[PDB]
Structure formats: C-alpha cells, structure tokens
Image (spheres, coloured by chain):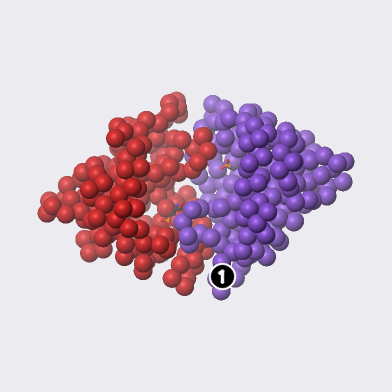
Chain colours: A purple, B red
Amino acid sequence: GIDIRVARPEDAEEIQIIYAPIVLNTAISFEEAVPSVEQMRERISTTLQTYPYLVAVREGRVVGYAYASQHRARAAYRWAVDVTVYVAEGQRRSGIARQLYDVLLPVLKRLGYRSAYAGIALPNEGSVGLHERLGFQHIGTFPQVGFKLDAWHDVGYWRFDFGDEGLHPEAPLGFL
Amino acid sequence: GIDIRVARPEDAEEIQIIYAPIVLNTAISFEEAVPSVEQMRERISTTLQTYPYLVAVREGRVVGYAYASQHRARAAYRWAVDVTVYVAEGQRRSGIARQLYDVLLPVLKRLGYRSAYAGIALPNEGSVGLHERLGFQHIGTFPQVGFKLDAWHDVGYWRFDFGDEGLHPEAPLGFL
Ligand SMILES: CP(=O)(O)CC[C@H](N)C(=O)O
Ligand SMILES: CP(=O)(O)CC[C@H](N)C(=O)O
C-alpha cells in the first residue's frame, strides 16, 4: 500500500501504461508521440546512470513513478535538477505523489543539488497545491509556450530550495 | 557603419574574440569551458541549418552577433524559440543589440514562431532595459540557479509574443 522502490528497466511496461494516456489525451506532457515499452526501457536505464528513478507499488503493481533529470546543459547549472512525478490515472488525490516526493527530494538534497524545479502545465490546481504544500515556490510562468490538443497551454515552474552555498560537484546516484 | 548580416562560418574567429572573455570572467554565459574557433565554426553551421544566425558589422569587423536556438526539446514547444545577443565588450551601450533584435525578431515571426524567450543572468540593468524597451515581458526568474565565479546567479526570462493562434509548423531559415 504505497511503498517506494528504486525503479528498474523491467518496470517499463507498467510505467508506459501510466505515461501513454498522458501523452495522447492530456497536456501534462508536452510530448506528442507515445514512446514504446522498449523506448521507456532505455530512458529508465539512461536516467539511473546519474539520476534517481523511483516507483510506487501497490498490491505488487506500479501505480506511479518519479525521476530526476538535468535542468539545463551549461556547466554552471549543475546544482539544479528537474523533478518529474506521474501517478496512475485514477489513484490520485495523491498521496502517491506526495510520498514519491517524500523520498525523491531528500535523496536529491544528499547528492548535493541546491535547487529542484518542477514543470507544471497550467491549469492544474491539483498538481499545483501538491507542490505548494511540499514547499515549492512558484517562480515564473511561460504563457502560451506550448501548443497541444488544439489549445495553448502555459507552463509554470515551481522551485524547491535545499539551501547552501559552499559549492561542490553534485554526486550521481551510484551509477546503476 | 552598423550593418546587419546573416552570419557565415568564416565569421567564427571574430565571434569567439567577443565570446571567449565573456565565458572566462563574466556570468553572462554559464559556460565554463572556453570554446575554440573550430567549435564556434560548427555551432554557426549547425544553427544555420534551422535557425537564423546574425552578425553586426561596422568598419569591416564584427561588433555584435545574435542567434536563435531551440527553446525546449519536446514537440509542443516547437513554436517557442530562444534568442541570444552578444555585443562587443567595448562597443556596447547598444545600439548594436537593438539593431540585431530589429532584424532577428521579424524573421522569427515570418518563420511562424509565436513567442521568443531571452535568458538574462541577473543582475544586468543594461540588458534588462534593452528587452523591456523592445516589448519583452518579464515572465519569471530562476533564483540562485547557477554558480560561477564564486557566486550564485539568478536567471531571468523575457518573452516576446508574436501573436497568432492558428498553428502551422515553424519553418527554418532557408537551410544551408
Ligand atoms: C509540460 P512539460 O512536458 O515541459 C513537463 C511535464 C511534467 N510536468 C514533468 O515534470 O516532466
Ligand atoms: C543564462 P545562459 O546564457 O547560461 C542560458 C544557458 C542555456 N539556456 C542552457 O542550456 O544552459
């Protein structure tokens, strides 16, 4: 009942089940083509080489996942990280989401990142409240920055601060 | 006498001369490695395959350049584009920058983009005023997102709305 494990490439099929509808029918993800199970399988592997990738299991099945990712490419951005959480289309009011974050965030802090950023396609008052009750501060919005499903969607950014200012290179999740 | 030209890889050298010290000792660019002339020569070629790359020439020399680049990776971001302008560290109080934007922006609009974004490392009253008097809206700031030269830097984003809501795929600057 909502236990959080480190993900694995074998969990690709159940992560795709969650992600496929989001891509086809929502503007939650700004992708337009559904990645295959094998494609999701390479993503998980690639991510785990440097970043945490978590899954939330319930009754022995994956009902949610969360992974971190590079914020930007330039060197001076290395203490910044993107965070991404998708719960399965129904077991929300989450819950699963807050928990996935309750594990992902402290692990991020340990590795040395100073800030975490979440992209939230607007409107999504449910997703917004979640982040804001975790401590995320809204720091900006890119209006009409994207076009999907015959509509112009804004993208807002929420920052989670870890603090600090001594500056040493962010270590990676033990290179899986 | 302040003339705006479409860049070509032969301008690589003079582009670096402007850009190399900016990387070494400013927070304007978050690159840490100083790019060579060959590296810059490949960036110009690659950019010109899809995006406009401009230079400002006066007295037969480059005094400012400007280029467009992909804003984000995912498909629904395809009508959004990043903009970058660097002028010569002695020919500023520009001038040059305004003339670059006077050319770059309308090209972008005719290419089918709906919004252009400029990322400004803060503080910079010089660059901020420029964008504000051109029509850019401040849409947010990423606080302490970068660390370089023993200091944490905020990055601001300014948006230039081209308008429209009919949505046809952005065309490239007549590919090389
Ligand atoms: C709108 P987008 O595709 O940029 C980000 C999607 C999701 N919120 C995430 O955190 O990955
Ligand atoms: C403020 P800046 O000039 O470093 C922008 C960096 C670039 N967006 C990135 O991909 O890191």
Left or right, residue B45 beside residue A74:
left
Q: Is residue B173 above or below residue A161?
A: above
Instruction: Bin the neighbour count of mark 1 within 10 Å (Cα to Cα): few under 14, some 14-19, many 20 and up.
Output: few
Q: Nearer the viewer, residue B60 or B85?
A: B60
Ligand 2 neighbours mark 1 (CB distance < 8 Å): no
Q: Nearer the viewer, residue B23 or A149?
A: B23
Q: Amino acid at mark 1?
A: His
State the residue at coordinates (87%, 46%): A1
Quadrant of ligand 1 in image: top right
Q: Position of residue B153 (x, y in %)?
A: 47, 64
State the residue at coordinates (36%, 62%): B34
State the residue at coordinates (53%, 60%): A78
Q: Pointer 1: what residue?
A: A168
State the residue at coordinates (63%, 49%): A47
Evaluate whether residue A92 shows in this view: no
Q: Quadrant of residue A155?
A: top right
Q: Chain of mark 1?
A: A
